[PDB]
Image (cartoon, rainbow over all chains, first blue to last red; front, top):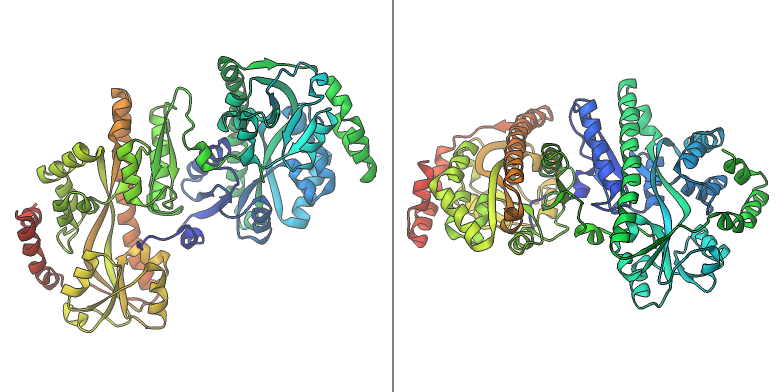
Length: 316
Length: 316
């Protein structure tokens, strides 16, 4: 074909005088996640005067998050994203932070992360898996679209609410009184356009990007899942760094994270107004009957694990 | 499986108040071409102070250069790279600038681009195909590796010189007295390692990235093909822009091109020393017998096309 090196050929080529960091992510070119990673790369090159460089591998081209995190464990990848709650697959008590409605908002989720419990989870990520969590970035709060108005929890009765295969999404739809319809992402839009399904749930950027809004006349601000992305660095990569480079990385990640978090909050405000401007009916149902409907979910969790993890988290 | 928008999903999503430009390229993540494109994106964001933004699509994920150039013609892609000489597929006289040894160095090639001949080609690019060429960036001079020294053109006799299945690389190997072996890029390393082939020819960065050096014992600075990349923007995209944004674009491209050109020159000096340090024997054979050996190719071209294209170009 053409004499052009592939991404695989260049992956392990190091830069001279500079420390080349590779970062993978599932999010695609054009996403806020990818844009913030680009900003992180530019800040690192600036703060380090070219001595730290960042190469980006989006769209899960290196594998999914499970594979990419393994690569950090083994030193084959330097940085990746992973949700705080996603740690639950490896450290079961971490799942508590992604049960529907446990995090009231991102300030609450941030406090969970920075607490002794969060530090406990982060210490175990590092001891077992060589995952050093540098920061948590707000990545959006899920809301509920639908083909009829959602003014109260009473309205979910008889709602066929699309939900992905994930356990907590399913817990949300069922414990709310709706009837969950598990389904792959690529089939949601159509399912809603023909009203083969009644609604779905996702953060506002996903609803905009997938154009779900044009097949849904209503949006309810259910605030049922607050999402984050942690920025994780491989511990083997970290210990190779001078204390100067360590500090540049920590400060660059904090700075980009503040901007990322602020950007997501900004986008959510614009999308609500964009959805209203398109004719969508936006409701703010009382959330307390949703938080009470999740109460059996919570004490179940605290029982099997044997510790009051969820109740601890709700008081933070 | 996951609720994560794809690159396809995000491609046509716009930014509010900002003009989203989309850039495709064959070069992969980690290449100098890709890195300069990220610098162009950062410069546009800063000089437009948020009003112009650039999304990058590397590794030919959008198609090859022929497909990407067509996408500019039709308005589906905004910016891409193409070699000045690559225009010869569409505008036949443009091929003259990539015949072996016509361009003595990049200053010569730049003068070719900026002259009335170059302006004539660039005008035809724009009139027929909606390609506005903004600038030309030096992209490296090809050199010759081998398993025995090349001190003069005489040494090319009986040399198994790998070349890609491309007209002008073939002409180089043939007219130099070597015996060309057309060959796909992916197999080149191995043929060289087992000495199944004697040598190849490529810019120094390709030689390092593919690690041909650990397999070849000699490097001859034959300087036989000076390469560039033009930065082309879709004319339909261009006319949508304000005169203010046009100038930001035009002059951001100049700044990044100066740095790209200087960066490729820096790497070439770097790699010659790296190759020597690895034990490679680096020769500087007299190039005049190579340029004379290309002479029947030149007037052949000037004859078929019917005008002294190559002659005009050599005197520039």
